[PDB]
Image 1 (cartoon, rainbow over the protein chains, first blue to last red):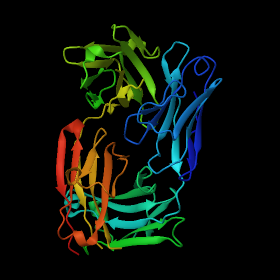
Image 2 (image 1 turned 30 degrees about the vertical axis):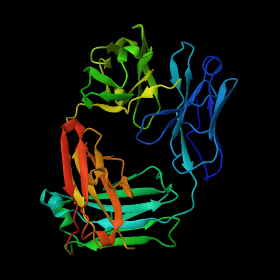
Image 3 (image 1 turned 90 degrees about the vertical axis):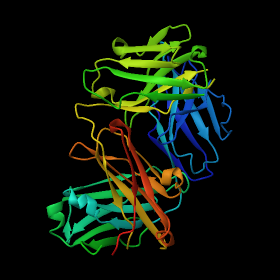
Length: 213
Length: 213
């Protein structure tokens, strides 16, 4: 069972997600479809190729043709962002699943709001300094964070992670953490995060001087 | 009807993974089939095995020599044992069962690793510096995943972003959780992050207060 890694469209539009199998799985057997919102279990949308369980709205539909099956989603809304899986039974009548398709809602561009956080005194006392730069509610996902410490570009000592699209406004957020030892943190004054994003006419920098807070 | 997995979050290589699925709101004896499916982080769904009302079991042939599924009618639960585990068995494990539409549990992450459990330290991301302020908690140096973070005991959900954890070069995870709130609230509204690292039985309620700058 193969499905594409991702699909995307604007709110109010339709997408289809196709599941390509073989004569001995989809070709002989019923197909089910599942929605997996981030952090939750798969939820059944369609069973027996085209049947909707109670409480699934008719924005979702399924069909099967030969060795392939297709889920349609009309009226796309914020909160449809999820991983969508097809499931069927194999030649042994055992469950098998497709690899998942991630649905992205194509909303309008939104520049991030940027915040910088010095390490807490509590953490410093323990010997480490985490400096955090937050990029809040932006779209699309592409964004670049550059750390500078007294104008020295930091390369390799930061890690970042990004949320899934938000269930209320379809944006992303990103958190970047710069790690220094306590002794190194106390060697420098100016800690700066510079953010590049299509929504910003030029890069935005948030910075603090060590010891002013 | 509620299904809930339970079991250790960490198993050592070569040892046996044991999970249980507590069924509530429904008599375990009445269920048509019960089964287990797993999902490696970032990957798709893999069926493990099923058991029918009769006691007859069917297992994934690639796992069959290591899998045991059984039901205890008296505890109203069913179980999964997977022997000789390796890092390949790190996954979220889901129990499911049919009572047309299977009930799924919420899943439980099992990490197979020779590293040991370590509880987090919780540090504030204190607000400071457009009428909006950002604040949060840094949940640092824990193993294995996951941690859960709520705000104000669940009363504060709007504007919260809890980021994917990052695996640090130390072998330990770090996670940040942030929220944006009205700047005018910072003097009067208490903000507490509720952190719960179940693998280490570590629960922390941390007040996040504005720093003095």
